[PDB]
Image: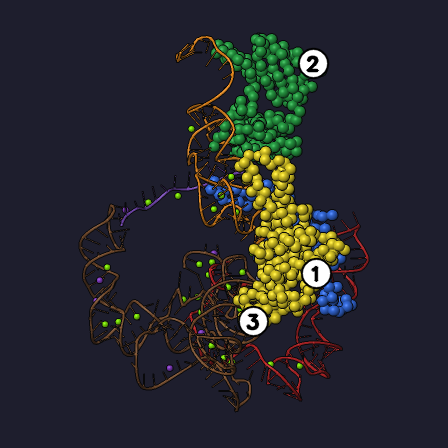
Chain colours: A yellow, B blue, C green, D purple, E orange, F brown, G red
Amino acid sequence: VSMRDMLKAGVHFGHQTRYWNPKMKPFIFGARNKVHIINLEKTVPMFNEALAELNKIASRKGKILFVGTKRAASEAVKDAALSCDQFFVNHRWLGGMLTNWKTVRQSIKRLKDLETQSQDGTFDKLTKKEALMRTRELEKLENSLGGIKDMGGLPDALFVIDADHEHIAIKEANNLGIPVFAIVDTNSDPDGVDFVIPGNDDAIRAVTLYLGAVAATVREGRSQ
Amino acid sequence: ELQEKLIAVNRVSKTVKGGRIFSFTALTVVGDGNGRVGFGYGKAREVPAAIQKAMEKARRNMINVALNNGTLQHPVKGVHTGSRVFMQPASEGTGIIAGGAMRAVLEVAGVHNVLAKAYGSTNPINVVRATIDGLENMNSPEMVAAKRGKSVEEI
Amino acid sequence: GQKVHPNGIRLGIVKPWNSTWFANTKEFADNLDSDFKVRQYLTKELAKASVSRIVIERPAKSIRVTIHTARPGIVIGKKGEDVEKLRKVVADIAGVPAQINIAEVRKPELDAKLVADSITSQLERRVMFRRAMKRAVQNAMRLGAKGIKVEVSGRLGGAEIARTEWYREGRVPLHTLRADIDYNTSEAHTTYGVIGVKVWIFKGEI
RNA sequence: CAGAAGUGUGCAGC
RNA sequence: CUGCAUGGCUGUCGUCAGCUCGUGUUGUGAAAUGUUGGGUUAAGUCCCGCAACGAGCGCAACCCUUAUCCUUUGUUGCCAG
RNA sequence: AAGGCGGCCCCCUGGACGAAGACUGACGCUCAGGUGCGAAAGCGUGGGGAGCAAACAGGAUUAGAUACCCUGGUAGUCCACGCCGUAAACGAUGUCGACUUGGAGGUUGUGCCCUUGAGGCGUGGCUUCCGGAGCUAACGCGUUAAGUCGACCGCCUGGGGA
RNA sequence: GGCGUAAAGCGCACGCAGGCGGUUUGUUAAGUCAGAUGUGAAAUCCCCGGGCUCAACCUGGGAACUGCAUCUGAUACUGG
Ligand SMILES: [K+]
Ligand SMILES: [K+]
Ligand SMILES: [K+]
Ligand SMILES: [K+]
Ligand SMILES: [K+]
Ligand SMILES: [K+]
Ligand SMILES: [K+]
Ligand SMILES: [K+]
Ligand SMILES: [Mg+2]
Ligand SMILES: [Mg+2]
Ligand SMILES: [Mg+2]
Ligand SMILES: [Mg+2]
Ligand SMILES: [Mg+2]
Ligand SMILES: [Mg+2]
Ligand SMILES: [Mg+2]
Ligand SMILES: [Mg+2]
Ligand SMILES: [Mg+2]
Ligand SMILES: [Mg+2]
Ligand SMILES: [Mg+2]
Ligand SMILES: [Mg+2]
Ligand SMILES: [Mg+2]
Ligand SMILES: [Mg+2]
Ligand SMILES: [Mg+2]
Ligand SMILES: [Mg+2]
Ligand SMILES: [Mg+2]
Ligand SMILES: [Mg+2]
Ligand SMILES: [Mg+2]
Ligand SMILES: [Mg+2]
Ligand SMILES: [Mg+2]
Ligand SMILES: [Mg+2]
Ligand SMILES: [Mg+2]
Ligand SMILES: [Mg+2]
Ligand SMILES: [Mg+2]
Ligand SMILES: [Mg+2]
Ligand SMILES: [Zn+2]
């Protein structure tokens, strides 16, 4: 990746000065039309370092969890996560999805057994009302958990799209001591993040660039 | 490995439309000796359930303290809420001169020789907080030297 | 408030009657009386043989009694020498000739009557009631009950004022008529008076 | 628009 | 004699829609959240949202009776031809 | 300064703040005792008296109603000159000085920029509301601190009695 | 150790005595620091040892007597 790629993606656009967080001050180049501009020549080396450590843990065969919740970003998140065989949460983050893993695993095994009886179990044996309600259960379980259904345990690292929106996941990962990689925007607080990646968290093309570089590095490390 | 202590049991209560519900709380500490300790506060409707929750909480939430061959590196002042705790290292064979709530913590930490005094509120929970805070602030010659860049011959 | 007795509400739905015979109004009361007498006798006799249940059937102007017990060899006696005494005394009480059959309760820990009697005996042994209750619940659950609850009532531990204490594990749907809720009650005669023990065990629906 | 008062004293649930 | 030493049984708020627990999280703590919010229902009934995720006792259903039909048997019941 | 100050005009008069310099050269801060100012009610002497209204009278309401409500009504409220010296006289927060992430507004100076405006960017004074670290028993405070410090003064030591 | 709400900021201000004092150079040596000398009665109190059949008691030596005073030096800080 190069600064021209990031400029093409518009990652330098921060938020309005009204909503800035002073902790981000070191990563700000300045303002234009009272909008903050993110310093790209700081971003680039930090992002390279983040990718280097991601590659390190990928070569350890570690399991990556991608996290985003945002209308358009969720689909690119899913696509990239599957593209590197890694796990994802792209709908609502459940409170306690990791710190309460010992519970949520029950809902995952429920999803598995519900799918197995749905497809192989000859689900048509049920009454129409029961079949309907159990299919709606299946739908909701899919939406909430399908991206981690096979994770089998805690992830080795979280990659996060918005440290201010997904702060719950960051705080849970800190509680568990798992390293957090996150895109951090001028309104976010970085202190929960181990590998801050300062940049716009809203432009779909910026998200595409970030997820692309991440998934490329993951595939690289997996191929070892 | 771990030594465990039960410091306190207290019966709290919730009022409800029908009357009073009584619940038990238990404060416990655990430690390896050798300067690792943690405390756990549990709640249940039964005393042994409260104690088991306290122990499970106290096996995580556990911190390291740089003990000086079984005493403190230097005197320390710890504070939490209303509880102020003074602790001072002591010569060998002094033993633990402390109150019960502090004696439990210092025993499971393995600090054989200490002088300690509680001031203000002796409330066991906040006393344990203040003692852990103090032990967590205590620092040792090697990392003081590392901070200041001197050799430890500076001692 | 009060609850319906969980066995009686399920009679004919999922629970059978413990007596089965047809009688006209003339002999009905005498049958019921002699059944009561034989039940009372057998309960007083076998008090340590872990008799769970007594079924009385009156075929062909005869009585036959089936005894369900978790300790069959004690009831049968060596070479069967004891059932002879039981059947003779039962023939004396009922007047009609008597037959006795014995059946094993394989897992007494899943029998509400035997669990209730166990807790009662332990209470009379001055065991701590908390331990008796916990042991009962844990054993029932580990042996595969779909659920259990137990209750003990009155002057527990010699306390000056009575209490009720109850403990529950698993699922216990008393309003579900399909539920085969086994239920029983027993009473411990401590030096302080009567302690009442109630046990409910759920073994699945239908 | 009107509508006042409620004798003393206790005990379990660790 | 003591229901103010008890068991069992029963009334009542009330057939009212409520009452709790595990794990997680927040608070020095008693505790809180869940169980609150927008709609909806006879109903903590159901759907969306949400640091909560699940579960239990309740609601509902299973049970009896009544309102329609069909098969089978047809006396001590019935009488279309 | 606080108590406080509200139609318009004139006379006398105090303080604050901003820009640019010039000047003196530690002349400063706090303050026991002391001195001054100090809402309303109240007091003295002389005026004025519309409205309002303690006291008081009558009518109601009520078990009663020395009240609440209604009809009246005196001191007082206003003016001049004295006295009194207290208030939830409150930010329930002593005066002075330094340091420490921000955001949105009000009011009043001033600099620069095509001044093009109902415009952009800087720099002072005072003031309102959120909130970060930190502090606090908690509530909360939060560059106008209840944060980190220094100087001086006033005050507290269980509830009643008081 | 405290003073927003638990007891506690005078209603506000001025100001004498008092407490406190930006920065630089020189000088003094009052405060401060160092050294020496005298004094600080014995007993009592601590330490090391003796004697009573042990102990309590008695007793040898030491330390201490946290101080006071007078000389001779230092001048960073404070005061002049
Ligand atoms: K009773
Ligand atoms: K909980
Ligand atoms: K003027
Ligand atoms: K004064
Ligand atoms: K009037
Ligand atoms: K009245
Ligand atoms: K008048
Ligand atoms: K007193
Ligand atoms: Mg105290
Ligand atoms: Mg009266
Ligand atoms: Mg009363
Ligand atoms: Mg009576
Ligand atoms: Mg409720
Ligand atoms: Mg609702
Ligand atoms: Mg329900
Ligand atoms: Mg909800
Ligand atoms: Mg006046
Ligand atoms: Mg007058
Ligand atoms: Mg007059
Ligand atoms: Mg009037
Ligand atoms: Mg006063
Ligand atoms: Mg005051
Ligand atoms: Mg604030
Ligand atoms: Mg301050
Ligand atoms: Mg007093
Ligand atoms: Mg105090
Ligand atoms: Mg008060
Ligand atoms: Mg006060
Ligand atoms: Mg004041
Ligand atoms: Mg002054
Ligand atoms: Mg003065
Ligand atoms: Mg002066
Ligand atoms: Mg000076
Ligand atoms: Mg001198
Ligand atoms: Zn953003």
Asked if ligand 35 lies within 8 A of label 3, the reply is no
Q: Is residue G3 above or below residue B35?
A: below
Q: Is residue A17 left or right of residue B70?
A: left
Q: CA gap, disc 3 to disc 2? A: 104 Å
Q: Which residue is mark 3?
A: A32
Q: Secondary structure at mark 1?
A: helix
Quick one: label 1, few (<14), some, or many (20+) residues within 10 Å?
A: many
Q: CA gap, disc 1 to disc 2? A: 83 Å
**Residue shown at the point (59%, 30%) measured from the top left:** C204
Q: Amino acid at mark 3?
A: Arg
Whether labels 3 and 2 belong to a single chain: the reply is no
**In which quadrant of the rendered view does residue C198 lie?**
top right
Q: Is residue C121 visible?
A: no
Asked if ligand 35 lies within 8 A of label 1, the reply is no
**Residue shown at the point (72%, 53%) measured from the top left:** A62
Q: Which residue is mark 2?
A: C80
Q: Secondary structure at mark 2?
A: helix
**Residue shown at the point (56%, 33%) measured from the top left:** C172
Quick one: label 3, few (<14), some, or many (20+) residues within 10 Å?
A: few
Q: Is residue B23 visible?
A: yes
Q: Which mark is residue A51?
A: 1
